[PDB]
Length: 150
Ligand SMILES: Cc1cc(C(=O)N(C(C)C)C2CC2)no1
Image 1 (cartoon, protein in one colour):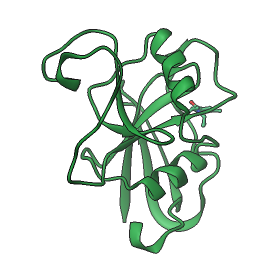
Image 2 (tube, helix red, strand yellow):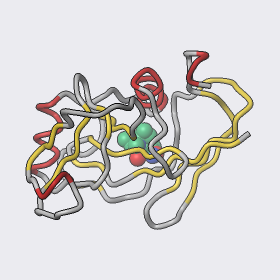
Image 3 (tube, protein in one colour):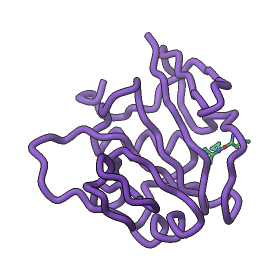
C-alpha cells in the first residue's frame, strides 16, 4: 500500500507534485494532497509570481480554478510551444498532476529537497516523497478525505 509523490523545487512557495509517475490526481484529491504539505492550490497570481522567479514544468496540474502548465522557454511538446501560465482549455478527462503553494517557503527559488509531509493524518499507506535528486522521505499515513479518490 504505497504512493510515490515526485516533488520539485519551490518558487515563491509554489511546487509541482506528480503522483505515481502518471496523471492520476482528481481536483478533490489535489486539495487534500496540498493540505498534507500545509499548502493550498495556488491562485493564478501566486502561480504567475512563481513563473517569474524561474518555475516551469512540462506537466498539466491543478491550480485554483484551472489546470495549467507554467512555461518559460518555448518547447513544441510542452503546452504547444507557449510561454507564460498556459491554461488547458479542452480535455475529455479529469485527472492531472497538482501544483501546491506553501506560504512559509522562501520567497524566490528554493531548490533544497523536501524532507517532510507535515500534515498527513493517520492511515495505512506508505507515502514516499521523491525529490528530483532522488533523495526520499517516507511516512505511513493518509491524506485523501474523499472515498472515491481511494
Ligand atoms: C521542514 C521542511 C520543509 C519542507 C518542504 O520543502 N516543504 C515544501 C514542500 C513547501 C514543506 C511542506 C514541508 N521539508 O521539510
